[PDB]
Amino acid sequence: FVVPDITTRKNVGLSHDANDFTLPQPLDRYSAEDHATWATLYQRQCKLLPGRACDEFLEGLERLEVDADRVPDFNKLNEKLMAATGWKIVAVPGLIPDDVFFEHLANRRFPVTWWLREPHQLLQEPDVFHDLFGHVPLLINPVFADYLEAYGKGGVKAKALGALPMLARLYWYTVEFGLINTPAGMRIYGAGILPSKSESIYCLDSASPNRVGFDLMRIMNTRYRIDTFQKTYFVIDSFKQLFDATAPDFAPLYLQLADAQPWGAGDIAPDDLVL
Ligand SMILES: N[C@@H](Cc1ccccc1)C(=O)O
Ligand SMILES: [Co+2]
């Protein structure tokens, strides 16, 4: 049997723009159970993350006043975020079209899935805990925020050249699953890792995954999988290094990559700096 997925179930009776796919955050749809689920996830992660999350992330939670005991009011958070870096979050029903996503980032709007996972499934699909808790705190960092805006603006060129998957790989291996080295050890900045109960341990503690120095061409030539822990994590030295490394013209890189065989998710390339 085919049954409606969680995105369809959660958005019953609600609407989305056919242009920018936003809706006002439906505060009335959050149950007591949702706020409790948020509180449980928030508590779990805030216990686990010290000494694992990069310090900028944990500071962002505090400076944005991300609620510990309820699903945050997006408008209230936006007061703090707009003052910091001129960004705002917008509510979306779930996954949105790539062009809309890029257009949002290009305009300093970060799309956040409004609804929350059920306590039964504390998942695959992005929810508000992943999108808000995982992605938003680093937007208070001006270099990271500029990186996301630049990434957004880059969507037009990528789409024109049939290279959106190459940009998607870059996003995945930085914004979603990135690690950052520090003198105190490796830390986490990827939004896919920070909300997780188990990958946050594995990515720093396990001998299994490869930890490879960031390399733009390598990353855009590297496949990924969505339903398993990462076999490779890419490591930056700073958000500045990441912004600068991604500032050159990607057009000739895309054309060269278009004609190449990509690395598998678990491969170590000949030129990898393995850490
Ligand atoms: N430099 C890229 C744009 C981009 C910036 C930052 C991240 C990703 C892409 C281009 O020429 O299109
Ligand atoms: Co994400």
Image: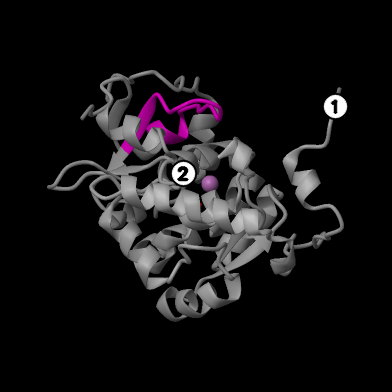
Give coordinates of residue 206: x percent, y percent: 28, 25
Q: Quadrant of the C terminus?
A: top left
The quadrant of the picture occupied by the N terminus is top right
Q: Residue at x 50, y 26 (%)?
A: 223
Q: Residue furthest left?
A: 183
What's the residue at 74%, 45% (across, down)? 7
* Three-letter code for the amino acid on which mark 1 is drawn: Val
Task: Specify the label residue 2 is tagged with.
Answer: 1
Left or right: 144, with 122 as reference point = left
Q: Say which mark, if any, is on residue 176.
A: 2
Sequence-first disc among 2 and 1: 1
Disc 2 versus disc 1: distance between alpha carbons?
A: 30 Å
Which is in the foreground here, disc 2 or disc 1? 1
Q: Residue at x 51, y 71 (%)?
A: 87
Q: Secondary structure at mark 2?
A: helix
**What amino acid type should be assigned to the residue bearing mark 2?**
Glu
Label 2 residue near ligand 2, CB within 8 Å? yes
Can residue 102 be seen? no
Question: Counting other residues with Cα less than 10 Å from the Cα at mark 2, is it few (<14), some (14-19), or many (20 or more)?
Answer: some
Mark 1 lies on a secondary structure that is: loop
Find residue 215 and report its image quarter. top left
